[PDB]
Image (cartoon, rainbow, N blue to C red; front, side):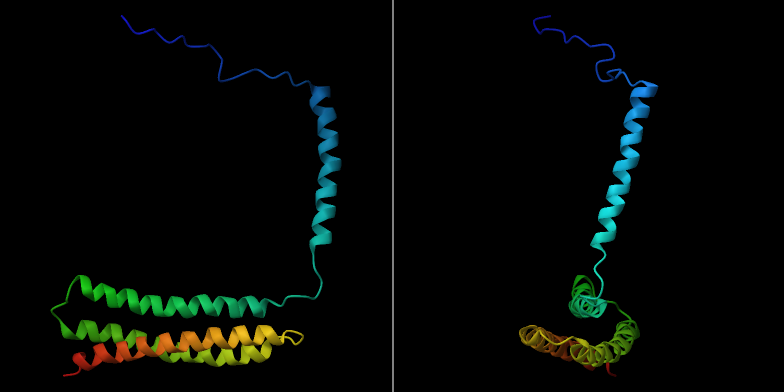
Length: 156
């Protein structure tokens, strides 16, 4: 036995900390008072009338915007992995996305409304929104064409 044997320490990983009823109870009282203060802080945080959830909604649409393309692109990538023998199957996928295309456009409708939904005093933010949507539309068009493109092969 050239190697040195390790010595295991008993109750080493579990140190018994002395916590008295009064000691704990005293600490307990402090915690209760402290808790009120935390609650006090929470009330202050509550900002009354400021950033509307719509902006976040718009923010959600932006992610969804990329998300919607991502679904079609992923599925587009998916067909890449393998090519189903049945033609109707691929066509069916197109149909679901067909509603999605129309659906997404409405979001575009809502998105336009959303721009109007945005509050004033933020003209610059307007420019950022306009560019973000314009970029999405270019990408969206490609996918649309891409979707249409697959359907063409799906036709007949």
